[PDB]
Amino acid sequence: DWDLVQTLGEGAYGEVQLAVNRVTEEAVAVKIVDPENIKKEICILKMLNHENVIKFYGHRREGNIQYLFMELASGGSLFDRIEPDIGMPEPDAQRFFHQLMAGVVYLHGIGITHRDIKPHNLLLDERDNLKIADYSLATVFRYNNRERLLNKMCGTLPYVAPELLKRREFHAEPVDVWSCGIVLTAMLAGELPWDQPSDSCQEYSDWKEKKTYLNPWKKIDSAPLALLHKILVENPSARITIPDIKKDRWYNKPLKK
Ligand SMILES: Cc1nn(C)cc1Nc1nc(N)c2c(C#N)c(N3CCC[C@H]3C)n(C)c2n1
Ligand SMILES: [Cl-]
Ligand SMILES: [Cl-]
Image 1: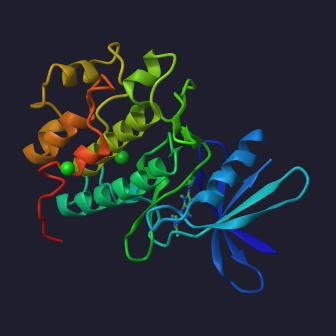
Image 2 (image 1 turned 60 degrees about the vertical axis):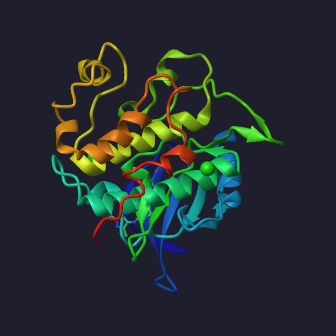
């Protein structure tokens, strides 16, 4: 059995605890759940094989409760590397963004959308490699080479793409690209640009009107800001795709550790 030493946090659907093995002292992260939902999460977790996606060990159920076993991320979360109102050194932000894109390209290539990318769900191993965690909202958007549109609102309001608040159905990939742009903003400014990307929200209107002399944008060097101008495009069909992010000037800029 296992000893639950502390809560690491709450996911989109449940709890996550630091569990220490009573016989081994091996420290792991365990998600303990009370349905159709967890059946789906486990199945997605089983598909995952990438250096920038969290390691799933396996699962155990006992009546009113089911247990999900994951690689403990010894570096904790990206959230804890963001200094409020400051962010982090631009070279650490670019490296983490390179790794986030590697993880998202992997997921999209196996037809999976994460749907809740934010710094809380991005963990760091002992060598500060980024791992995309929390598959509680993840779903299939491509099967047998056929795309299906999403038609369900979920995620986290400051990270969600505007089409998810406006369209009955929308493409999965541009939504995950948007959330990656808000994560890049967070890493470079230590502040979220808006509560939600709605015309009711003045900070979002100011961005559409290009007032980049306001915060958080004025904290952001012109090169990464140019990338953010192509990611945070309201119309998903005009938003930059990952293959063109890989071509961006800042994305390809050599920066010093
Ligand atoms: C060693 C360590 N110190 N601290 C403060 C955090 C860790 N390491 C760690 N390792 C994980 N494996 C997860 C994990 C998952 N899975 C998780 N989460 C919280 C709820 C959302 C989810 C991403 N969190 C927060 C995780 N934290
Ligand atoms: Cl933040
Ligand atoms: Cl090309």
